[PDB]
Amino acid sequence: SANSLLGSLRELQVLVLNPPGEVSDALVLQLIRIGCSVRQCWPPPEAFDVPVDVVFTSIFQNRHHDEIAALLAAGTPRTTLVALVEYESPAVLSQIIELECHGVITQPLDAHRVLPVLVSARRISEEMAKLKQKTEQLQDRIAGQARINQAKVLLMQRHGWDEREAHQHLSREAMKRREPILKIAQELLGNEPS
Amino acid sequence: SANSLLGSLRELQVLVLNPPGEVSDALVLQLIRIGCSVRQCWPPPEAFDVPVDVVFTSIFQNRHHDEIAALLAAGTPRTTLVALVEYESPAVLSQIIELECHGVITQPLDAHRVLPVLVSARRISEEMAKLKQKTEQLQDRIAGQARINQAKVLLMQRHGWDEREAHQHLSREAMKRREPILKIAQELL
Amino acid sequence: RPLIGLLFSETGVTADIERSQRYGALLAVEQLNREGGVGGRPIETLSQDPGGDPDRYRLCAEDFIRNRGVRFLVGCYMSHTRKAVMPVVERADALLCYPTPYEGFEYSPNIVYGGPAPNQNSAPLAAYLIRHYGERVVFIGSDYIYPRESNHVMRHLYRQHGGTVLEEIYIPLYPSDDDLQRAVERIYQARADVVFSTVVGTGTAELYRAIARRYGDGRRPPIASLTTSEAEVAKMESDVAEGQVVVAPYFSSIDTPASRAFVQACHGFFPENATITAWAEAAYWQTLLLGRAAQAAGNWRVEDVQRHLYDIDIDAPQGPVRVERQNNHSRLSSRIAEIDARGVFQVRWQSPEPIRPDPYVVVHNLDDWSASM
Amino acid sequence: RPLIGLLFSETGVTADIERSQRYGALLAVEQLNREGGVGGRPIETLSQDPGGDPDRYRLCAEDFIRNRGVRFLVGCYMSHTRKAVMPVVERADALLCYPTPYEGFEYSPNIVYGGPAPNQNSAPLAAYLIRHYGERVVFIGSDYIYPRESNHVMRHLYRQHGGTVLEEIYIPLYPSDDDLQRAVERIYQARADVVFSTVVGTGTAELYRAIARRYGDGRRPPIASLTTSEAEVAKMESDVAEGQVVVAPYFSSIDTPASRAFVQACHGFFPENATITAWAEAAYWQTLLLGRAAQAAGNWRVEDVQRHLYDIDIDAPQGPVRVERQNNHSRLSSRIAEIDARGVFQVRWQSPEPIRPDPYVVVHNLDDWSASMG
């Protein structure tokens, strides 16, 4: 919701992943005026040790590129990403595309750019993440039905059972073992197969 | 794809849906320097007329908001949306959220802010459209797989055939009647 | 220099409040000169009239900076006029004092906010109205950003505390008699317990008179407003104004030594067409703060003067005020008054201590005010 | 006050080319002052040495604009030094002339771009290289945005036209000895047909000398550069420099009276440690344009001067130039030159006419250059 998105900003945990300096100070102070919980962080760590909702990062061409790209790829699925951009040139815009930013702030930044990009980027990252998840849920379901299907067919052949028997066995085995019916299929299976 | 995205900016058809004036002017001039096909329109129409890939608009507290909203609600979902924003207060921001922009440019606008926002917003809208397309494909696929599997069990059990035999038969009839395996399967069911 | 540019309309829809802001600053400049000017010389002022037009505030702001060497400005009232000037002062590294209430959600390093953000006047007013008045509310505002943003906050507040927002009506700045008549008829058919007004400038007096006459005799719902000042109330007849509720850091009826000094300075300095208001008080204390900060810096450079202004407390006519370096907004008193039968503002509630500004707060917790109300 | 602020390093990694730009600009001022200055008043200049540091450029621009009333500036070389100054000039409504080649993708109402965008130098150079040299290439550039953006385009161009980019190497801006030796060994181990360099400033000469010695003083791959200037080639032994390839709008060897007049003027005015370069040429013509636009306006108001700028096509040493009002970039000649044994720049190809600037073009169509090069 517009009101639930606007009302949740003060609970967001924000990280400013940028070398300490004027850009970083202003950015952190505006986020503190908005009311977000904020922290700056330089050199790029390997992993974040504390939960993070939104990351603000600069775009590097040296060794910090691969560090930032690896760290951010490790993050949680609803991590909002905003890029601090200083160039509109191909190598720089390609990196923003590759990082999958949800919003951009062009430099030099000032206080006025912050909130509109933050809210905006946050509805985008929330929508995208729900869409992605649904895709993943469908993929998972497709693969899982395939595996259960091939374990049933495996049981039919092995035992001379029809489908009902095969299905009955899997369920009974799954039900009384406290393991999903897909677990039994996988434990049964191992055709080194599909 | 970052490369193809950048390489296709000059074929984008961009509409500046905003009142005539300095803001529209400066925005249209920077979209022509970037190289996009750019038109400007005002008052908001009811349907586009010509295909539009990206719309830039402002946030109005009046009837153009609803017009613009309806205009893009009915429009092609791959139309990227960028809002020019001058206030950070809750009713204005709620308007941005309800329009579901793919990117924003806070005012006052200047040329440096345009290209980075147009590209990041375009990636965003295209990635959304792709996930929705994958969702439909996967929904259809799960359903298809089920009927191919229930039809296979049907043949297996009807004829005393193994899975492989049922699969060979489906494929054979399918590819002899120039139709999808799924059609054969649904015919059987 | 020391040359202060005064960017306040003398004409246009908010001329009555901006003329009094302008005189509050002029009065402070007169006082600053009697207290020694800056680095030996007298502080001068240069005034320009934008007529309530945002494009003209912009052009005059540019004229002040490009052609008059001005780097200190005191001005602006409606929020679109502040937005128009902000970029001009930010690019020049100038400083504007904005002695006016607003919607919050802004931070500029170049603007000193002397009037309340919504946590300092709308939130408390909401708490007050929900405690003492009916749950049926109709809203009426001037059609521009501030009334709209104010109403967005107010309607959420009423809906979340058991009330019903029966209608949100918008009339243009400078309404026609037709506009007023249609608005009033809708106010009357809605049958509210309270009228919440965000109507700004010319046409406020007439609106209130037309509400009064539409009901004739018979209980008429009271009008509570975030925007009506003393200048609009002075244009009303006594019985039209009676019972109305207004909010501000300052009212001219305050009976404190600092408030009485201010009233007497205004009565000896203001021309007759300029009524004392909360925004004249705001423009006054801000200009004084600025001149004193300049005397402490020993020069008239923005960086040096601005530094020193975050550290000086001012005993304003309203009470003690200070500007917080973290956000450029001010610690302000907050009062809700009811007009009596003789046009005088009777304070019915005042925040126990100055309210600290929090302009980006989204969720106003009205429970904050339950103990002092 | 007709006062031009000159923001060019005197010290630091690009000190040679920027001293070259400073004297080109000073040469123009002097000529403008012999033509009547600006309405009877002589044109003055103010110089500060930012030493190739982007933060010092910003500070010098800020001093000039804030404390000296400067509204007209000439300066900046490496792109991040331009980025550091840009915002200061835009907030003050000042005008900066940037007489430097760059990566493109920029439009600033307050910047007059006197050096080529990629469609004016890299593209033609790419066509040329793919046409005459083998398609296995090795890249070496200084580690900052311009060489990186320039490599981003060249990498894509070679792969599209059947080439192989074997190694893409970056060295720091003031490269240590080890940096060079490691870089040259990689270049030597790749066995490339061509070396495409984007190395800029101090260390360029040493780089080319180390490539030279490294190879078995034998039919090394030629070095083609987008960055090397006459200032770098003068520090090179004759045999190292020989056969190397370089691109620019201007070369001191141009065979015209206009070019001849510029050489002579530079020889009798520039110090001993300030070589003529294409960027001295650009500082000269831009600074000259400023003066004539001001003379035509009758004043020194940015607005008045600026208006008269797009209308004055000048006769520069390189040939005829103009500034386009649509994008603040210029119509520039483009020459590709091969250095002979006596250190002289032999122009091998020239665009038939000045190339119109298109700073945002993403797909450089190399076929554009087929007719004029083959």
Image (cartoon, coloured by chain):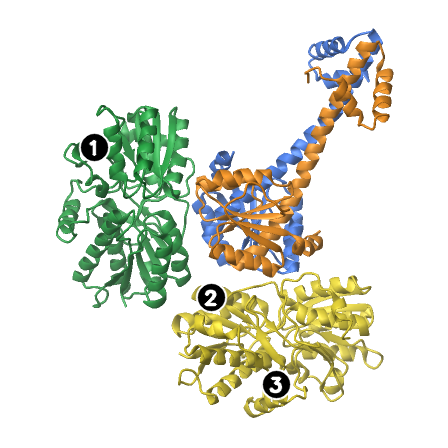
Chain colours: A orange, B blue, C yellow, D green
Q: Say which element carries label 3.
A: loop
**Residue C117 rendering spot, x and y as whole percentages:** 63, 69
- Residue at image coords 80%, 17%: A152
Badge 2 or badge 3: first in the primary sequence: 2
**Residue A90 rendering spot, x and y as whole percentages:** 44, 40
* Residue type of the residue flagged with mark 2: Val
* 1 vs 3, front mark: 1
* Residue type of the residue flagged with mark 3: Thr
Q: Are marks 2 and 1 in contact (CB under 8 Å)?
A: no
Q: Residues within 10 Å of mark 2 (few under 14, many from 20)?
A: some
Quarter of the C terminus of chain D within the rendering: top left
Residue at mark 1 shares a chain with residue at mark 3: no
Q: Are marks 1 and 3 in contact (CB under 8 Å)?
A: no
Q: Check residue D240 in the rendering and tell me which mark sits there, or answer none.
A: 1
**Residue D258 rendering spot, x and y as whole percentages:** 17, 47
Report if residue C142 is visible in the image: no
Question: What residue would you read off at disc 3?
Answer: C275
Q: CA distance from mark 2 to mark 3?
A: 30 Å
Q: Chain of mark 1?
A: D
- Residue at image coords 40%, 82%: C39
Which residue sits furthest top? B160
Q: Chain of mark 3?
A: C
Q: Check residue C88 in the rendering and tell me which mark sits there, or answer none.
A: 2
Q: Residues within 10 Å of mark 1 (few under 14, many from 20)?
A: many
Q: Say which element carries label 2.
A: helix
For residue A29, side relative to residue C368 (left or right): left
Q: CA distance from mark 2 to mark 1?
A: 55 Å
A184 lies above or below C290? above
Which of these two is toward me, D361 or C117?
A: C117
Q: On the image, which quarter does residue C140 sit in? A: bottom right
